[PDB]
Image (cartoon, rainbow over all chains, first blue to last red; front, side, top):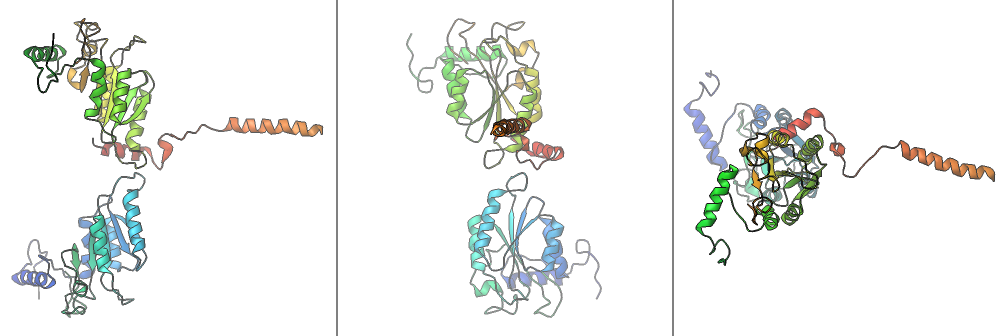
Length: 187
Length: 187
Length: 51
């Protein structure tokens, strides 16, 4: 039951590599990573590649872990109303036009954070419109799906299966094993 | 007495290259070019490397040929008072901060145009201060010296000789042969 | 009435004084255009610019 320590020095076994490969094949991506906790995963994911000069556009009903991760990252935050896509497009256009605050220089990058299925409302997000907008305006997409990775879909692949969207359009896919698979952790 | 045509298909002789090398050695640069007229030289020089997104900072008492060349180029123009360097530094700082009009994006480049000796006033320009400013703020320098290339200096080299400034600091040096050498043309 | 003529002069003098007390302003203003800046911040913009 004991583990050696941090994975960078000791604590990696063949079971870990097997699990990562199996998850990557199951989801349909090319490579993946496995973590022991989901809240920590979200709270520590964002600061690795985001900076003060970037912009994050997110919904108003996201989980607390995403909010904590964005707070730790230090980037600018803009929010849009739940279920409004005209407002989202207007916000994206405006933010591209204006630029950075007080200097009006262009942003280095823009990231869109959304959630697959919302537990408090039980509603789905419109993924094809987000894919179309990110293709048109050259933006990146991040999808949070912990309630829909195993319980929804014709075969249980996730939100990308019911809509028929190719998995290669979305940049980062994340989920947790707690809800449906009976074990704790995330990927 | 007859020539062939434009100096790209026929009309170049060994005398042309000899004059090229002689002028280049006399001035102190590495290479040069010789033209048949000076007004045309100034009126056609600027549009080759300047564009709508660049900025030109020039004195208020420049010759007409420079004004025509800058008008044909299409870049933005800012002017400073004669003999004031505090105003010049303030203008450079403000223009660097503000950026392009109506978009506030940074300029692609900045160029400084001045004259070696002014015929209407008979006064010299303070070259060392210009060199210091261009080194500190990363700007480019253009010097027009047709009245001072052969008549001034301990040996007649120009304005760069009386001040002791190395010729490599200035970017582009121009002059005409009409005033002192008894023949028409420019370089 | 006579006080009306004096009131005209008073109204002219008041406007003259008001215009005299005002400060110059131009459309092509200085750095104070945005301004939302401080001396420490401006140096960062100057150093960040690359040609």
